[PDB]
Image (tube, rainbow, N blue to C red):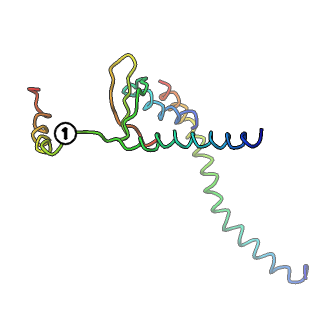
Amino acid sequence: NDKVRFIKDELRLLQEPGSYVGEVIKIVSDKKVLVKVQPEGKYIVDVAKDI
Amino acid sequence: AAPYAAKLKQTENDLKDIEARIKEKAGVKESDTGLAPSHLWDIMGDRQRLGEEH
Amino acid sequence: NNNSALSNVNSDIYFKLKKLEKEYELLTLQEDYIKDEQRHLKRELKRAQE
């Protein structure tokens, strides 16, 4: 049961929209942060409530 | 060197408090200018925002 | 004491276990079901991997 039902949760994860590797150039204190997605453009964008 | 040495050590603890204040103070920001006239533009701009001609 | 009015100790163990063996048929029923569950789960381990 342990082997078959771990896999079904794992299907969701692999089927992500994609996700990028940026770095924060500088912070804005309205909980937005200037993040240069590194091959792509610069974006000022909000965060999660995990950080 | 206890008479000047001790006292020198307290001076370094002070500086660290200061640097910390610049960080603490910077934490409201919040600097968007557009004033009182542009409170009208935000209604106008919701219609331009769902405009495909921009 | 322990051997005087022994036929009264006899009747309560006999009664109590007789009731429980009906309910202990429902636990072997379960043994039987989970022999099948693993066979259904073995084809579903295959389908999940598929």
Position in image of residue B48 (x %, y %): 11, 34
Direction from residue C42 to residue A41 in the image, left or right? left
Q: Nearer the viewer, residue B42 or B5?
A: B5
Residue, x 52% and y 42% (percent of image)? B18
| Direction top: furthest residue | A39
Quick one: label 1, few (<14), some, or many (20+) residues within 10 Å? Answer: few
- With respect to residue A40, does C27 lie above or below? below
Q: Nearer the viewer, residue B38 or C30?
A: B38
Position in image of residue B10 (x %, y %): 65, 44
Residue, x 59% and y 43% (percent of image)? B14
- With respect to residue A31, does A26 lie above or below? above
Residue, x 82% and y 79% (percent of image)? C7
- With respect to residue C32, does A36 lie above or below? above
Residue, x 58% and y 37% (percent of image)? A2
Direction from residue A17 to residue C37 in the image, left or right? right
In the picture, the quarter occupied by the N terminus of chain C is bottom right
Direction from residue B15 to residue B9 in the image, left or right? right
Q: Chain of mark 1?
A: B
Q: Quadrant of the rendered structure where residue C24 is?
A: bottom right
Label 1 sits on a secondary structure element that is loop
> What's under tag 1, amino acid-wise?
Gly
Q: Which residue is mark 1?
A: B34
Q: Nearer the viewer, residue B10 or B27?
A: B10
Position in image of residue B40 (x %, y %): 10, 44
